[PDB]
Amino acid sequence: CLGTIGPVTPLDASDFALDIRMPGVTPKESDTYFCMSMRLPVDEEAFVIDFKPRASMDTVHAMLLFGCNMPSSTGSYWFCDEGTCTDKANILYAWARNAPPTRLPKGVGFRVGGETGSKYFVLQVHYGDISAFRDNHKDCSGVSVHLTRVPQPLIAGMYLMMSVDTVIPPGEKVVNADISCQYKMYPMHVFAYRVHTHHLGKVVSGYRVRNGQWTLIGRQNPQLPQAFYPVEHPVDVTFGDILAARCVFTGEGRTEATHIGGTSSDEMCNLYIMYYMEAKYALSFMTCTKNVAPDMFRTIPAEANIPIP
Ligand SMILES: [Cu+2]
Image (cartoon, rainbow, N blue to C red; front, side):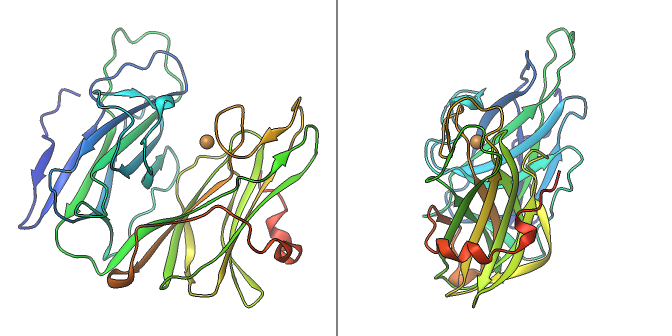
């Protein structure tokens, strides 16, 4: 936080590192999410290929890195409750304390810059428990990013699944939020995933369904750290398969109905599926906001319901 490392350190011929650090912030209460931005130094296309977390051990619980064109603020920093990005927050990295970080496979890179690519990174740093004192304590937590202009042969992106149609009535023991779209692109290979809900979430499970056979992509309690969990053996998703996902909620202790689709006195059901695709057929993001094949869930594997506390 009195370091001298610089915002751009050119590496070999065609690479560079970007040090994305909080500008000396001071978290005052616990559970605080501060956000900041770095613009890419290049207008042309570029490939994020590695990450080094540089977090203050003492207090930082989680870190997220996003790629987007419109950060919710132009200030040196802001509370992330304001928003992350005004446009798509294309999530690229998540670090949790104790979580394994998930390393990109050799030759996989996120595509940024140029025409489609995100022009800004937005870093989100989550501070759990501050101590009482620490007079004026400045913190410069963040991440360094390895960019290269050398074209990568595998491109990574995010397939996002979200539920927006389903209500949790109060006191209802167990409620299933279900999500499914047909896949219609060139092949993706899912190598990681992260889940997200708020406090009524019990388990999130993601599948590839091919000719009525379910293959597990990943499965997790969303009350654990929302880092990216690795997929033991990467699952290939190809044309005509179906992605299906099930969030299990409860409505216990809840007074009125709770809606799964935004705000804060709301719930959410998101599965972030991180993939790669051969560069020439690739795209950086895909979304599913529907349940096209709802009856299919009568055959969901039993593992999808058994909780993982
Ligand atoms: Cu949320």
